[PDB]
Image 1 (tube, chains in turn yellow, brown, cyan):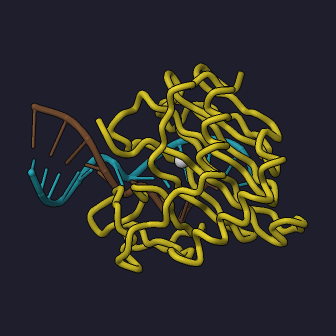
Image 2: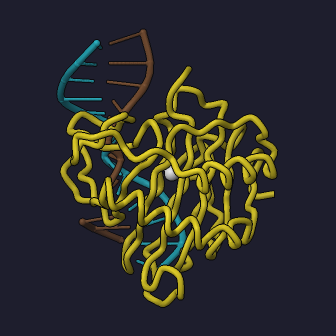
Length: 202
DNA sequence: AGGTAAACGT
DNA sequence: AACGGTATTACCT
Ligand SMILES: [Fe+3]
């Protein structure tokens, strides 16, 4: 048990990974990866894009979900069926049979790239979990608690691993340590992560 | 009266 | 290099 409400499902997406990676390439050929700039003016080391009906984005004013890619001025690409199917099966296996994501943020890590501890809290309906799928190079995941200083668990996430948090762990701090260089036959020299969220409704 | 943004030194 | 300060404020609404 990763924490109350939280599971790691090791190698859960390993058989779906080839198709997932083809579809990430397709998503990116419409809304390219870009390193976004925080409100305070720093360029993130992780490159990002989104698919689905809502996409996570930084603004001068803060963070937000938008139906429009602000770089292309066009809707984000539709969420691929391969993504939505894997998400629905991982959710179900982790105990969240009703999750309906309408947003998928896609992170790409080059060697050196990191994601500092943060909370996912931009979603209006905190009852829905987050589903996180890992592809390519391995990375160390930090998973804390409700307070930034709460002790961290560190876990290696390998190609195909899926983590799901929700309920009591929904607002826990988490992040990614600087990516080590290396080789993966499917991604060559990077790691991808797909994070599914329910970002609309109410 | 409340909610947000946060990505250098030891 | 793991931990924790910083937002301990200054803006919105
Ligand atoms: Fe996150």
